[PDB]
Image (cartoon, rainbow, N blue to C red):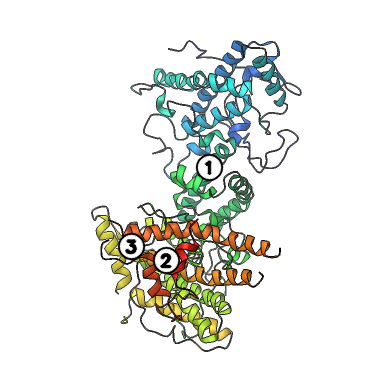
Amino acid sequence: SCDLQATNYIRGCQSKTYDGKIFPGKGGEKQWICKDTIIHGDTNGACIPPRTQNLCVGELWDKSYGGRSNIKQDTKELLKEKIKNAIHKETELLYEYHDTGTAIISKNDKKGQKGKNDPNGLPKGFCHAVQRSFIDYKNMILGTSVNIYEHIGKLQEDIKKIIEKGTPENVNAWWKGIEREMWDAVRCAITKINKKNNNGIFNGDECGVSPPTGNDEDQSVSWFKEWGEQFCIERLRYEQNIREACTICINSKSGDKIQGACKRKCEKYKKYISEKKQEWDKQKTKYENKYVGKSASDLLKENYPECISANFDFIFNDNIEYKTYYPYGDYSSICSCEQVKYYKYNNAEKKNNKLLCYEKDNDMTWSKKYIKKLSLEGVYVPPRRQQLCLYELFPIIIKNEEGMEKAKEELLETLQIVAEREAYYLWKQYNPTGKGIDDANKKACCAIRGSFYDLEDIIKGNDLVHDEYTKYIDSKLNEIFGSSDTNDIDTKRARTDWWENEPDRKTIRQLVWDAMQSGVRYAVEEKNENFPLCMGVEHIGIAKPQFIRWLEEWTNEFCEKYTKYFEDMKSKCIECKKACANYANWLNPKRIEWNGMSNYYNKIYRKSMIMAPTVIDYLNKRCHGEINGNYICCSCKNIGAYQTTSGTV
């Protein structure tokens, strides 16, 4: 039902070149620009996409010399028609650009041209590109600190004139009203491809009925999502190339090194990351400042299915020790000739790389983020759970795609390493934290047991947090252990069985516990101290449900930190006003956490009663008196009986 210019020539609006020229052409590739420019201005932590830099402005602006708007002597309907034509031509141009398979987004990860098409007959990436382009029209018609073209700012103020001299900021409103008719330029130009196609039916609603959503309205995030889609899409291409040269590595050195095409393919990725890190580092900092509590890594992992195998924390690391140990980061384990093996405590010669997890932060807070789907709302994640030493597990899981024996073989020895390192580092955190010596390690033997159980729940697939790491680990373990033929029920029982049982008499649950004693043995050896009794136990009691374990962790901590604050405030009791400000500053997020945590307890037990005691009651038995280094791990100066009055209103 549109009479708008179909086989139209908009001046200056020719075929796209941002991702390079369409063959037989070659080059003209525009690059992401993140820094401030004389041409574009302040980006403000943002990176301008090449797709943006090639926007079809056509008759609205002229690039000849400095660049000037033609819009000066235009009317309101004249200006709308121009925007409508420009938008319509940009979709047409973006059809060709993707149908040719020139746009990085329109590329495949292995299969040349084969399988790079969505449900409809529209090329891979066409809709995303068109959607993004539409947002750029919106932001260009309104006010933006980034100038897509050299002097285009002039156009935005001239637009003001037209809209101010019309029937009724006013333009922020004019776009609001005009936007539907502007999006229909996208839909009606999509209808045109059907006429071109034979038995390939089109109607326009294939890229959506309405113009891009709420989240995307923010140029900054629309551009960041594109950066993400492209990074992931390119990253899987670097993967395939590493996999064609490494699984399909010659020990040259004095020892096991990659040297041929494998070194070449891995270095190509190592170089790729070295480049893309600045763009990430910038856009991460700016996004997360614009959206508190929101994670960059999430905005991407959600929207783009190619990002599933991606872990930005591991790819884009600031840790020097990591950068050398994992030189290819993400694909390090694949780009390594070195045999995946955990070395037992008094194994002659060769020792494990206790190649540090990040420095465990004591100042860290509890979190309701990265929590599992199924409600589970109310539960808080402990800080020492958040500082999990399961980093080594991520590259090795990426390595083994075919989840056969080798996958679960390599995972087992990597589990033992992860287990050793965590235990090593926890001792170094909790022993310098403890009061007495026979109390410092008594406090340490529990953080260890906690993590042993949490590490256990992760593998068993019983854990309550699918974070930057554990999310893909759950997905891959379900791949490795369960088939499509066997439901989740057998899959849960597959992981639980692998861990619980097993050459030697030792089980996978046992080898992980043995490995944890080894880490404490090296930690205590360093300080020339004696290995504790709480750590020397062949067996660890059956883990309590994670929620209840974590609820005890919360309570033990609160009790200590309360008797710290309240006591050091009362002692100082004006100067109290600053002590009160601190005590209350700490306590306010505790009230939020206690309500949530104690509410869950009742939902899972007490409420529809059911022969279960109260939250306080349970914790009263659990925290009365001194600590034990095994399953008796909570202590309070005053029993929880007062805590609900302390933590409410």
Residue 345 appears in the figure = yes
Residue 551 marker:
2
Image position, residue 357 (x, y; %): 54, 68
Nearest to viewer (mark 2 / mark 1): 2
Residue 59 marker:
none
Q: Which residue is mark 3?
A: 404
Q: Secondary structure at mark 2?
A: helix
Label 2, label 3: how many angstroms apart (C-alpha)? 37 Å
In the rendered structure, the answer to whether residue 441 lies left or right of residue 403 reads right
State the image quarter where residue 38 is shown: top right
Upstream in sequence: badge 2 or badge 3: 3
Question: Up-down: is 411 above or below 115?
Answer: below
Nearest to viewer (mark 2 / mark 3): 2
Question: Up-down: is 15 above or below 393?
Answer: above
Residue at (63% x, 37% y) in the render: 48
Residue at (59% x, 45% y) in the render: 287
* Residue toward you, 622 or 256: 622
Identify which amino acid the numbered label 3 is placed on. Answer: Met
Nearest to viewer (mark 1 / mark 3): 1
Q: Quadrant of the N terminus?
A: top left
Identify which amino acid the numbered label 2 is placed on. Answer: Leu
Label 1, label 3: how many angstroms apart (C-alpha)? 31 Å
Upstream in sequence: badge 2 or badge 1: 1
Q: Which residue is mark 1?
A: 230
Mark 1 touching mark 3, by CB under 8 A?
A: no
In the rendered structure, the answer to whether residue 594 lies left or right of residue 325 reads left
Q: Count how many numbered circles sit on residues in the image.
A: 3
Image position, residue 403 (x, y; %): 35, 60
